[PDB]
Image 1 (cartoon, chains in turn brown, yellow):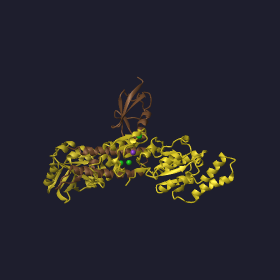
Image 2 (tube, protein in one colour):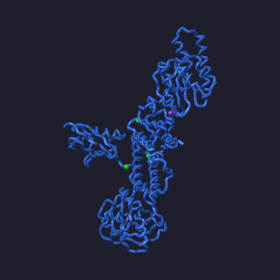
Image 3 (cartoon, protein in one colour):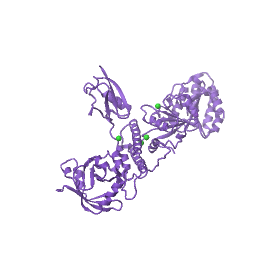
Image 4 (tube, helix red, strand yellow):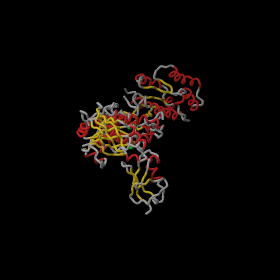
Length: 153
Length: 421
Ligand SMILES: [Cl-]
Ligand SMILES: [Cl-]
Ligand SMILES: [Cl-]
Ligand SMILES: [Cl-]
Ligand SMILES: [K+]
């Protein structure tokens, strides 16, 4: 009737909200951002493919009980391309690539990326709290890449 | 510019042997407007060296980072050794790849069921070969891809990859013997991305791990206990209720987490309360027990290497002041004699481990006892890297509010516990 339950998710973590349909989503967005040490502008919330501004209300978007809002972090360097960079090898004239040779490569690529990310911290204007959550995000992603590479059948 | 074809010589491998001269229809790219920078490069290109390779399976799974621009069948104007080039692609079950500055090329045969579907290769079959053009990758990335042979710091099969990543991130838990712990204790403010990532690391090693502000007393009793404080508690760690008990129970302490100062151990991993300790006395104590300094002197001798006694530089003038205040009509000849004893224990460097607080170290308070107790507290915050214990001898034990990490004991307590050794 007066309130609705919403689910904000970034694919890995979900949070539920109880808010009036007549109140601006600014509070909901800035709340979610806080739990990730992020600024509200550092993320992008979108409901049904469309983005949401800080003044639009659940009444505007005509949101319904138990609906979802997808939060999307801004891509981090070339993080998503790392495992692909490791798979590349010399043209097989005589030898053939090994699945172990790929994981060992991924180790080197994960190393290069890290050393570069850390070295890049001077150029970062973000706060400590926000860069910390990111470093942890990077490592969990890199870990996921490793598990996926070793899963190749 | 009137040409509709991208024509080039194809060389392969470390021998750079000539496979042949090929053509690729780019007329579908001339109508577009977004890839002019790309097309100009394609045209001026007259030679393509295929030196790298990637399997089909890896492309299907990790190839989405590529941005497809155009795909089609290659045309052979001249065939020097294309047969061999085909055989190798088929045996390798993959595609030759070129990571250029202005574009990315994939070359594979029509026998490659995987890639024929992965890139919707349809239309005119000009030859057994097919090519796909993607947008170039960031310079930095291509560079890593070339240095992707071997890591500088090798991953060990016995360690969890989760810890190895932390290791690369300059948090080397193995260097501090963390993985021989009998209990892990993790503490942090919220939100706590690092703290709970750390919990994961140790839960993987099957080491008993607990996280939170409220830690049960029983968890400190293990043989080899590790206490990890997140950087977010670097200035409030003396609010942890369990701090002193932990020190008593021979726990090892570490600061961990990303820190930005300019904006064995590792950079984002730091020891706390390593060894030794600091001892100070309150005025209320110096009066209840005048002999204190010369009476705990022997303890300082033994611990001359890991311990120090620390008094404020104004300690003589401090006693005197509070001696007059307390006893306004007490004789003066007695005053000088009591003061000479302190001045003597400071003036004459009898002990090398008898230091004086720096003038800017003293925390001010109307009560001298509160002042000295607060100065030691501030000393723990600024010297947790040099000393483990911080003991304050004071007349009445429950007269001062406890400070986490400190031992506020009267002489008798100090006598039975610390001096018994
Ligand atoms: Cl990312
Ligand atoms: Cl990292
Ligand atoms: Cl915690
Ligand atoms: Cl870090
Ligand atoms: K213990």
